[PDB]
Image (cartoon, rainbow, N blue to C red; front, side, top):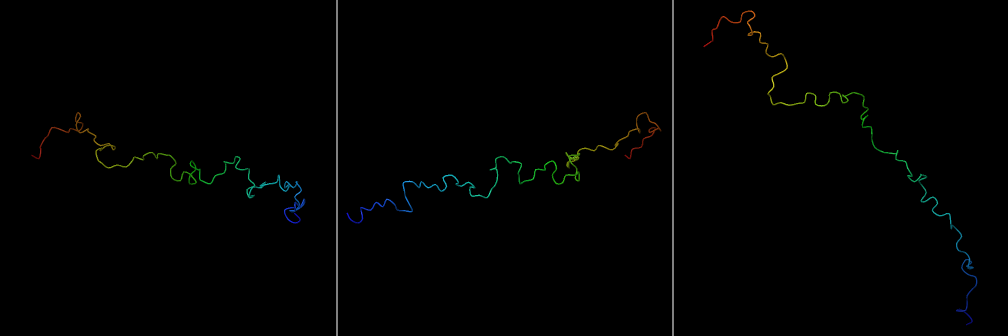
Length: 110
């Protein structure tokens, strides 16, 4: 009861006076939050992008390779025959009412 067990030391440990309460920060804490950013916290900046969007103006579009001009088939491409039409094919005239006389004679090879 003379030494030890009876040592409350009303003062010890940097100070310890029922006060302290650590007034260090109590406010200024993570104010910069890992710093590095100084940004409005993506509050609203969609205008920022990292991809092409020149769909209408793709590849310095400048009518260098037809820009929707008769490019919806271009006569297409097929090969199956069956057609024969376009240029003034037949012209008759040889018959009708005989102009320069296309009759009055017949001699079949056989």
